[PDB]
Image (tube, rainbow, N blue to C red):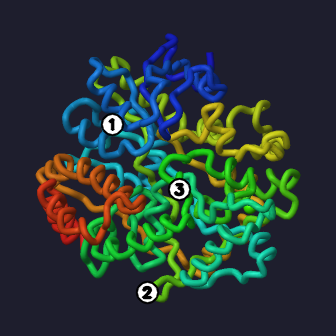
Amino acid sequence: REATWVTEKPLTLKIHMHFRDKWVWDENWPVAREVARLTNVKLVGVANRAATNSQEQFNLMMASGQLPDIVGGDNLKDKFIRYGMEGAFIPLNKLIDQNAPNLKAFFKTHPEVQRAITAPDGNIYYLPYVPDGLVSRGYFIRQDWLDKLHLKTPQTVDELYTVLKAFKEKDPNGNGKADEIPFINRDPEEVFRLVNFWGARSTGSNTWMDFYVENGKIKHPFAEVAFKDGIKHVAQWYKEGLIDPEIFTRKARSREQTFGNNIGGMTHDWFASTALFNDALSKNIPGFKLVPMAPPINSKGQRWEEDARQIPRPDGWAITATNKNPVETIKLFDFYFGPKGRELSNFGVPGLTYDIKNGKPVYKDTVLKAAQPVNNQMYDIGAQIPIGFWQDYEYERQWTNDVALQGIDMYIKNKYVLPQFTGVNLTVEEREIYDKYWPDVKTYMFEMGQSWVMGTKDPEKTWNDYQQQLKNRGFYQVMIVMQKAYDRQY
Ligand SMILES: [Ca+2]
């Protein structure tokens, strides 16, 4: 028995957790096993490991009969709220106030986080993934390629065009072949963010395709005329091969592939893991130098960094109405917000991935010297996963090299990061319109966006049909309630 046990009698619960379109909960994970040992509660996964879309899996689970005991994953906030009000997920307010002292304290000191996860009916239907940090992404460019081609760091979009064209046509890796791919990215959604170069927004926060506010008015990036004009430019860059032709399909290992084979010239991604490639590829590609770059001056005369860490994220886990042990479950959930629980969910397992030295968790050299980014290494053993947990930036600091640190400092110092959208508080009736139309409009917007970038549809010629479809699909009904809810707060 352990003082951390949340139940005297061993308890096993079923969890459906499919995340980042590639992973599922693994009861064999070192972290899962350690938490089970300490709490006496074991979670067994029931998600389909042979599936490449996490949202589709949530929907499939919801239509495959009786739900499991717990459901977790990334980008599920809206589903947790929608189905929570439908009775599929239970309210946690009471359970927390009565059995979770760590969470109760956390929320008292983090009122903004509590508000962000609360539903229109005032109920909390899930515990969020709470990131720790300030900046997230930044632009990175191949300094060695710039040097080899005698080009200066691009300061404007026009200068950037010239530089990327040079990367594509001037054989910077010197193998006599036109194999270079100027701009690459792990996230297909980043291709949409390129409209920033032409003064248009792509999202209001770290949450993909989120709304934003301008002069007291709620707006959505994909519906603005600025997007039409901006995406036309992105389409041109894609047409000319300045943007990875496989940008919508390569995905997850784009960096390992393109930087690893010395064909990638630039990206926009997280500072720590991206800068790590300088160390991982130092042996195979001497001179490889991927460095942070300030955003180029855009068509509106400004340097924009649209992304920032979002606290909390629309990720996490919830308790279903079929869970027969809600009290034991919330106690398990609370364990993660305690000192030991937070340490495990962030660093892995003591003696395996880290050791306590001078009272502080310190990653082993084998982890820090690995070619794989530390967050990827954590995913592999059940840490840094999108359950309800509190991220600790100290875990990240340990593998943020000087190149990354200096990039982070530059972005913080020069204030490139745009104000982030912190959401609004919808009434129950307003939420009904949101859940009825938004999901499908969002999917439609992505589809149109991809068509415009790839050239299968001309944004200029299809814009009217598009706006008509947005109206028919309920987009403006959603915009109307969003604005009303906004005016209530401010
Ligand atoms: Ca070449």
Which residue is drawn at the image coordinates 64% and 81% (left, top)?
Answer: 154
Near-viewer residue (193 or 395):
193
Task: Answer with mark 3 or mark 1, whichever residue precedes in sequence.
Answer: 1
> Alpha carbon of mark 3 to alpha carbon of mark 1: how far?
46 Å
Which residue is drawn at the image coordinates 52% and 60% (left, top)?
Answer: 309
Q: Amino acid at mark 3?
A: Pro
In which quadrant of this rendering is ligand 1 seen?
A: bottom right
Rendered view: 206 above or below 224: above
Give the label, 1 or 2, closer to the camera: 2
Quadrant assignment, res 75: top left
Give the label, 3 or 1, closer to the camera: 3
Quarter of the picture holding the C terminus: bottom left
Rendered view: 195 above or below 45: below
Asked if the residue under mark 1 is in contact with the one under mark 3, i.e. CB atoms within 8 Å, the reply is: no
Q: Which residue is mark 1?
A: 92
Rendered view: 380 above or below 166: above
Q: Position of residue 370 (x, y in %)?
A: 80, 43
Quarter of the picture holding the N terminus: top right
Near-viewer residue (192 or 369):
192
> Alpha carbon of mark 1 to alpha carbon of mark 2: how far?
46 Å
**Outermost residue to the bottom:** 301
Q: Position of residue 82 (x, y in %)?
A: 24, 41
How many labels sit on residues? Answer: 3
